[PDB]
Amino acid sequence: LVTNGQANAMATVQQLDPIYVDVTQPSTALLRLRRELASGQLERAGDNAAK
Amino acid sequence: LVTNGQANAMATVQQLDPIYVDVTQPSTALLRLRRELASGQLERAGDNAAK
Image (cartoon, rainbow over all chains, first blue to last red; front, side, top):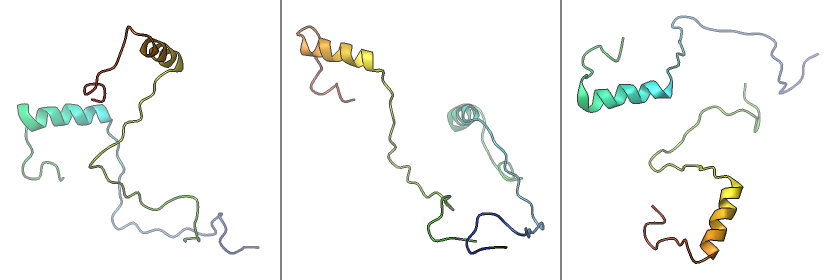
């Protein structure tokens, strides 16, 4: 038996032509990245923050 | 599938232009601060006590 608006699934379809990747960086590394990238040493250009 | 008013959300739209800061302070220090403020030794300023 199956009912309207239930919570348990009954099949699973999924597409795979691109596939996402959910990576995690810590929030301390955001500050260590941004404080040195804004003023001091390094900068982003080209395909740097893309590929 | 989407049900009428389900539990979980779909996307979180949030505005970041001001931000709130939920500051936790213990209660015994708050009693000590209220006692020293009701007494005549320690008092708060008129313009620097909200910054």
